[PDB]
Amino acid sequence: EPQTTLHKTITPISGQDDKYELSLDITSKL
Amino acid sequence: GIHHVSIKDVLSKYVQLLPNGSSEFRVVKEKDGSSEILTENQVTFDTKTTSEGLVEVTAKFSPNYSLEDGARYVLKFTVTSSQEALDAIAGDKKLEAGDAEGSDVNKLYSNKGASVTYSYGIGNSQTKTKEYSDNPTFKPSDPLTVPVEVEWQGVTGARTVITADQPSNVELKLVQKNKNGGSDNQDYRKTNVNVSKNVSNETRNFEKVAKGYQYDLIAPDVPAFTKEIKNVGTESNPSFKVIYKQLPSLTIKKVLEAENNLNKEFRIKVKLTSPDSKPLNGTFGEITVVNGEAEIRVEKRKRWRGILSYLPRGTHYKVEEEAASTNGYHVTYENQEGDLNKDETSTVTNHKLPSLSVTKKVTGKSFKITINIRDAQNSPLNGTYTATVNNKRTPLQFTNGRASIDLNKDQTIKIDGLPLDSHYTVEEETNSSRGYQVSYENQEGKLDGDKSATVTNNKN
Image 1 (cartoon, each protein chain N blue to C red):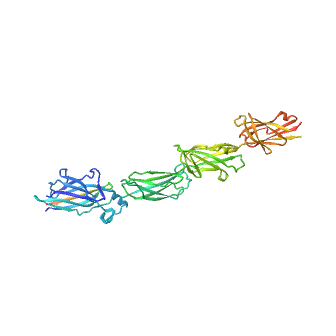
Image 2 (cartoon, rainbow over the protein chains, first blue to last red; image 1 turned 180 degrees about the vertical axis):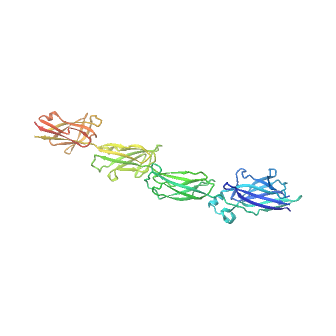
Image 3 (cartoon, chains in turn brown, green; image 1 turned 90 degrees about the horizontal axis):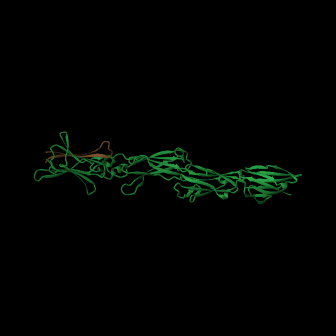
C-alpha cells in the first residue's frame, strides 16, 4: 500500500484582522 | 497511485467561511518546486452542516484522479473568527473542555476533526481514512476599548460658567445592540465618571468590548441640563461624547420707586410659549406653569423677585403685572418680552403716582381755587381722583384739565394718583380773591413726586 503523510496548519493572514488560511495537505509515495 | 481521494475538515464554532466563495477553496499540487491549481474537472468542493451543527468542508477529487507520486496536494481556504471567538476574547463567553489548548482563548482550535479518505488497488480497491493528527490553534484579534468623554457646558456654551447644581458623578453604560432579534444589552459595560465643579471635560474607557456589534451609550438625565450623546468615532471603532448643557432661567424682578411703604405685595404674570406652540406645563424652580401661564407674587421677604429655573431653550416669555397690582403706580418694564436663549432678567418698576397738595393761608369764608393739569403727553386731564381734606376722602373730577376746590383758612387738600410727569397750575377764582392780595408758593410745577402749592390771601 502507498505511504501517505498528512499535515494541517492555520496561518493568520498578514494585515487582515480575524482572517486565517487553513491548509490541509496529503503527499503519497508508491 | 491513490485515487477516490477526499479531504475533509470540520470547522469549530470559533471560525466560519467567508461570504459568497470568498473562502476561495482551492487544491494546489506542488511538485519539484512548481505549483498548480486543480481545475473544476479535477476537484469539487462541498459544504455541509454536521448533525451537531458544525460546518464541514470537503474537497472531493474527481474519482478517477490519481495522486502523482511524491507530489504534495494541499487544500487551502480562508476562515474568519466567528462571533463566538470575538465574544470569548472580550471575556463575554466561558470556554468549555475541548474549546482551546489549555483553555486559553489565545489558542482556540480551528478544527473539530479533519481527515482524508482514499482508495488504492485496481479491481476491488482498498479504502482507508486517516485523521489529521495536527490540531491547529489561533488567536482572534484584540477586543475594542471604547472611549467616553463627558463635557459640561453653562447656559451660553462651552467653557461658560455653570451655576446649576451638578451630581458628584454620572454612571455611563455601553449598550450592545442585539443583532439577532433579541433585546439590547443595556448593561454590557458601565463606568462612573467623576463630576467636579469647573472641570468641564473628563474621560473614561469601556474595556474589552467585543467586536461584531453596534454600540450605543446610556447617560443619566441630569436636572437643569439637556443631554446630547454622539458617537464621535465609527460604527466599528465607537467613541462617545456626552454633552450636558445648562438650561436658561428667567428672573422676574420688581423695583419700587418713590414708594416708602415696602410692605406691599405685587402679582406679576408671565406668559410662556414654545416655538412649536404646544401649551407649556411644568414646575420650574418654585414656579409652576399651567397652560403657558405662571403668576409670581413678589414682596420684601422674597427679595422682590421670583425665578423660573431651567425653562426649555427658546421659550418665548411675556411679563405683565396683574391689573389689580398696578393701582396707584406708573408701571414700566425692562426686557418685558423675548426668547429665552440665555439667562434673562425681566424687571417690573412700580413708580408711585405723584400727589398734589394745595393749602389756603389767610393773613391779617371759603376760597375757591381752580387746578389745571395737563398730562405727560401735554393733553388736558379728564378723570376722577381721590382727594382728602382733614381725613374726609372725596372724589375730585377734572374735566378738560380743570377741577376746582374750596378751602378755608389753614386747610390742605391732598389729591392722590395723578399722572407721573404731568404739569399743574393753581389759580384762585376772581370772586374769592376780591378784598385780598393773593400770593402763591409753587403756583405751577411738575408732578414728578409729591408737590405742594400754597395760596396766600392777605386782607385789603
